[PDB]
Amino acid sequence: EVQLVESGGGLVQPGGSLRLSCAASGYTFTENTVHWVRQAPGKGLEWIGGINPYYGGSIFSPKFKGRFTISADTSKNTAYLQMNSLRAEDTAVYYCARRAGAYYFDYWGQGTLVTVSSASTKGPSVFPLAPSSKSTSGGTAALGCLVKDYFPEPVTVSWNSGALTSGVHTFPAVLQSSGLYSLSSVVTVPSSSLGTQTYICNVNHKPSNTKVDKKVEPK
Amino acid sequence: IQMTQSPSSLSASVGDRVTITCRASSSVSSSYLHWYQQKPGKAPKLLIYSTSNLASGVPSRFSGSRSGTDFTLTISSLQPEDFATYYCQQYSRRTSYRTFGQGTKVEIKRTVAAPSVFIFPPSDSQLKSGTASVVCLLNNFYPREAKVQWKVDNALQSGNSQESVTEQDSKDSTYSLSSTLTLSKADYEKHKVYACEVTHQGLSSPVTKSFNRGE
């Protein structure tokens, strides 16, 4: 019942600043310190710092102490990470985590990706990958969605608003020659269901506030 | 206090016993060394705390111990859902600082599985925009090494396709691959036969999927 949910990530120009939020619930916010940990793409975990909401003070790794601040607003059960003078090496997934027991992190947020870049945001174009079999073919069929020319990462792709889960593969994005990302999301289904079950691919790219729902139909 | 984690990655079959070691330079109390499991795209999950204590709901095939300067996470019977990257964490009481090991990726070794190949022509919607992307999908295979080669009117393509491989599946430990050939509307409309040819350790003969622009 304990939950930490983050928000705030996105695209930021170098030398700029950004503020991330961590909403805590399911426990008395004042009885547990809250920390931030980042993870560069492909690299490992790195501790940033933490705050004690009972007092309001914070510790920092010597790598970030001058540049980042951590505050907490106890009335909203929220912790905040203010990041200043951001550089390309600050591009990473940022997590909040609650400390409990002998100084372990027992509840983590989902992570929010921060990208430090001077390129402008680009919303994705969403195209169908029409199913391979006909409704009379007899086996399994593959169908999909192409999410082209967006920036920056990430996009969230789901199928039938998340009700369709088994057999779904959303591939890692690939940085194209143009400098924009592109990925595909496929699902395999029974051929017989092609004429009756609606298949919709929901794409959400926050940086550009794009929410597209693309229906995939045969032929 | 700098942690050193080993190995960087390992491959083991289902039912095998894996061990990961974090060597703590300096002296860390057994109470302040923990182990986390991170599945792809997810947040780290606490597996073991204070060297040897299992977290709630964590299967007891996980265990941990310390032998001097060295800490050890052990999975007694490896299972496919254990595919993850594992991190140790240490807390120092002098400075309140935390340090993480650099991580150990645990891949599952399984029997060879041949891919299922599908080909998707570009959509009319995308052609109305001036570009054409042909997609080739390899579904649920092992091992990961695969070769997808594009042929347009039997001519071999190069430098106009990008591919992408999923992480290992947590159910059946397979991979999937997506290869995208991109052309302009002009070039796409100037050719007729489009094929991807796949070679994989599980295929005795390469598999070809193709369509003809039109039908």
Image (spheres, coloured by chain):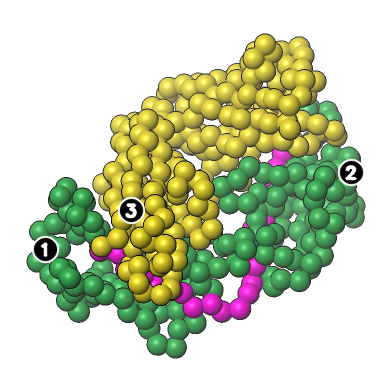
Q: What type is the residue that disc 3 sits on? A: Val
A217 is higher (above) or lower (below) than A7: below
B182 is higher (above) or lower (below) than B206: above
Q: What type is the residue that disc 2 sits on? A: Ser
Tell me the residue at 38%/27% (across/down). A13
Tell me the residue at 15%/63% (across/down). B188
Q: Which mark is residue B189?
A: 1
Q: Which mark is residue A216?
A: 3
- The chain letter corresponding to yellow is A
Q: Please give the residue where the numbered disc 2 appears in the rendered image.
A: B30
Neighbour tally class for label 1: few under 14, some 14-19, many 20 plus, Cα within 10 Å: few
Cα gap from disc 2 to disc 1, whole angstroms = 67 Å
| Residue B19 spot, x, y in % from top left | 78, 62
Which quarter of the picture shows residue A4? top right
What colour denotes chain B? green
Does residue B124 appear in the picture of this structure? Answer: yes
Q: Find out whether residue B104 is within the magenta segment.
A: yes
Q: Is residue B106 left or right of residue A28?
A: left
B186 is higher (above) or lower (below) than A66: below
Magenta segment boundaries in residue numbering: B99-121
Cα gap from disc 2 to disc 3, whole angstroms = 55 Å
User: In the rendered structure, which disc, 2 or 1, sits on the residue that comes first in sequence?
Assistant: 2
**Labels 2, 3: one chain:** no
Tell me the residue at 76%/30% (across/down). A99
| Residue B41 spot, x, y in % from top left | 56, 47
| Residue A52 spot, x, y in % from top left | 74, 19
